[PDB]
View (cartoon, rainbow, N blue to C red):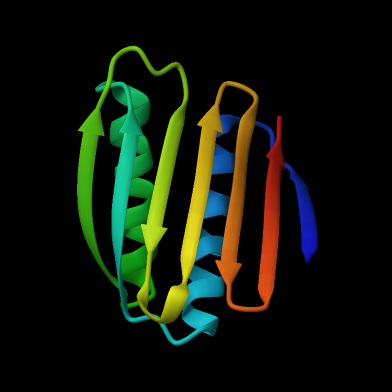
Length: 115
């Protein structure tokens, strides 16, 4: 069980670094495609999170199947990425930054992106 913490200047940098590291860990575990579920408001932040992940997956040659379940009452974004053979990523996005929990059988990585 490993915790990693990073410092970014802004939420935009948090989104970019987190998407890169998330795709990294999935690429490590032999993932070529994954299902993405998004929970949050239908706004500009939602669009940014989509493009950052899609651009990051595209550069890595990974296919994504995205479902957005919009709920305006949610003040924060939850992302659930499911991959084959038990690969699961949960990313929480708020004004304070991003916390991503990357789960593999016998491997739990928690990534925090502060400021």
